[PDB]
Image (spheres, coloured by chain):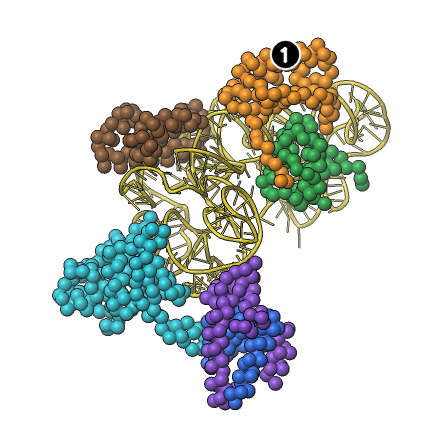
Amino acid sequence: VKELLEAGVHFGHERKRWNPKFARYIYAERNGIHIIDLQKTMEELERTFRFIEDLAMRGGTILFVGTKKQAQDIVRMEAE
Amino acid sequence: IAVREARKLFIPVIALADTDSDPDLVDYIIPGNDDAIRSIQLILSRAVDLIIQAR
Amino acid sequence: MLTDPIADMLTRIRNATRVYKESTDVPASRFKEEILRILAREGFIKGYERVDVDGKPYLRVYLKYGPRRQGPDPRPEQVIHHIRRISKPGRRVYVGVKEIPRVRRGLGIAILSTSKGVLTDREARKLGVGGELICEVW
Amino acid sequence: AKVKATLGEFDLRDYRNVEVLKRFLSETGKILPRRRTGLSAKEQRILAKTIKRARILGLLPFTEKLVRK
Amino acid sequence: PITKEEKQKVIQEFARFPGDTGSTEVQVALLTLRINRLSEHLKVHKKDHHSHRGLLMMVGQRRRLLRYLQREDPERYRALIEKLGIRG
Amino acid sequence: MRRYEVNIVLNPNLDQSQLALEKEIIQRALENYGARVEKVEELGLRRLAYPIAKDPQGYFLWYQVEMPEDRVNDLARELRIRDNVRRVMVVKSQEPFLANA
RNA sequence: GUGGGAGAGGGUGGUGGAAUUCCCGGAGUAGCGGUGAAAUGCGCAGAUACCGGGAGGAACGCCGAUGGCGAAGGCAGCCACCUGGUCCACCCGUGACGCUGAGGCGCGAAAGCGUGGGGAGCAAACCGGAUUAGAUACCCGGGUAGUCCACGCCCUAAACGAUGCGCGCUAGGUCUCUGGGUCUCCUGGGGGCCGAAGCUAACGCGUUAAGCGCGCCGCCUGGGGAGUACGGCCGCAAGGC
């Protein structure tokens, strides 16, 4: 944490869109919005970063696929 | 479509999934935000930095 | 009206195990407990616990799945592929020692309520007793 | 606007409260639907029953004529 | 309509013990009272086929409870049947 | 015994003599049928939305009464015998369901 | 059991308005009516359109809903009475008293029959006109049975959700009707719409299953012949099983 919380990572969608299979990650519901348990985010993030670093050091290629509106620029800049 | 294509060819999947997603289709998952430019920025910057450093 | 409890328990286990849920709740009884203990000892379920739901005694069954699969449909392989009820109310099935069936060449099991308790087919043949044929599981 | 909105507190079951019940009728002596009134199903039902009762008493018109084309 | 007072008198009359409202005797007595009222009503109103279904359901329920009571405790069954004047 | 409301719409073209006469007649019939009045409201004359008995006016009488249910019907058929009474409405006393709370 | 709720659920008495028809009164003239176009028809014995006073029969305009109630068939002007089912809360009483149910008993749209009444409008059959190789039909003007009420029969249907009943288990989202609560919203019941798993030949169904199971009942075994013939039972008959 201490970076995730300020970045608004732990903000989900309303109760009108949540996929039931995602329920294992949700901490609690506030003011009609779904909040993600940042702790589980921490362990999962550690796991995924470990995998990413291992694959990169092995020389593997990772493809970035984000085609939303706002995500275009960030994806381009990061991938380049 | 991308995720289904990656599944079909036995390619690992990493996603920045949020509340309205199915975690099963993703092998390595980051439960966080997909809106909120700041969240995307943090996650992607960290990942790219880790890529660069561990080369 | 609930006519068969044991079929109910088996169906509860099945329906649960297929939406890949983690635990399940079933009303408690001695006979159900015997069947559950046989299932657990055979490495079919993670194990059973005695709990209380609003005072009512219930049994919580913890369920076992395989490793996560690769490619499309990555849902883990089932440990209980198929679980039936042989002897139902309105048609009771009893077998001698000679008539004890073999399930999937021994890869599966069949549970009997022999005169010496609830036993798998293997133990019942070893002891040399028969009785009601409850269920087949593999 | 909506008739309920352009009103204060009142009692629907009063079958003699003419000065308000006159508002829930069109130019022709017909009960206004929930589109024009803006009431719940229950309120609308009670209102229709009350209007019918008042019409029986002769307080309200069964039918009228609009002075137009 | 069956008044609160009549219901209460029946309950207090057929109670197994003071403060009982659920014993077989109480239920059978209440059913008997309902059956009586509905029976006379249907005697007057002949073409009321809808209430006849209610009557049949009531009679069936009473018979089921009486069967249970007779199976369990015969003395109470005979006492109740004589007290209420059923089947006679 | 239950609680009821009684509405009488009678001839407007009755003077004091006939008005008090008919009032006494209906009242006498009221205690005849075991009724028990809690309050009386007179609304004088109000304009009807359509003619009743060839006249556009009517005199309104309102009585919140209390009487056994079984007689109520009979009571109504008694209040309608007078030629001067145009409308009789007996309504079980409902509850003030307050709209727009 | 106690405290409450909703509703075109049923039966029996009454009374409210707007039409249609007929009778009469006031005037008031030359056509009304009808069709794709026209006639048949009504009118000069005063038709039609207007106003006023009567009689009578049947159905309830707005509300009105993709809504509610009932086991179905079905049920809506308003008021009162006598009653059936159902839901919620309190978990207060009894102690497995339960589910299904071949026969039996009862209810069962419309049409049809019997004994009486009633008859405004519509209208099988029937009588004319028109369209037409022919219309014995569709369109038009009349018109009995019938449609309405009481009692008694008949017992059928695309009587449909083309889906028997009871119970338990298995993601959700959304729109409504109706209750209780601490009322941002949680918690029961009912009616719909998308859709997880799963099912299905497919269409599609999917917590109101056509999913996973259990208990009981009823049916099916190629299409015609044929719901026919025969025998039986039920009906006044048509006819039904």
Amino acid found under the numbered disc labelled 1 = Glu
Colour in which chain D is drawn: green
Q: Which chain appears yellow?
A: G
Colour in which chain C is drawn: cyan
Colour in which chain A is drawn: purple
Q: Position of residue G105 (x, y in %)?
A: 35, 33
Q: Is residue F41 left or right of residue A59?
A: right
Res. C96 image quadrant: bottom left
Q: Which chain appears blue?
A: B
Q: Position of residue E32 (x, y in %)?
A: 34, 28
Q: Out of B21 and G22, give the one closest to the viewer.
A: B21
Give me the chain letter of mark 1.
F
Q: Out of B33 and G233, give the one closest to the viewer.
A: B33
Residue at x-position 34% and y-position 27%: E12
Residue underneath mark 1: F24
Res B7 visible = no
Using the image, determine if residue D69 lies above or below residue E76: below
Using the image, determine if residue G160 lies above or below residue C97: above
Residue at x-position 47% and y-position 85%: A54
Using the image, determine if residue F38 lies above or below residue B28: above
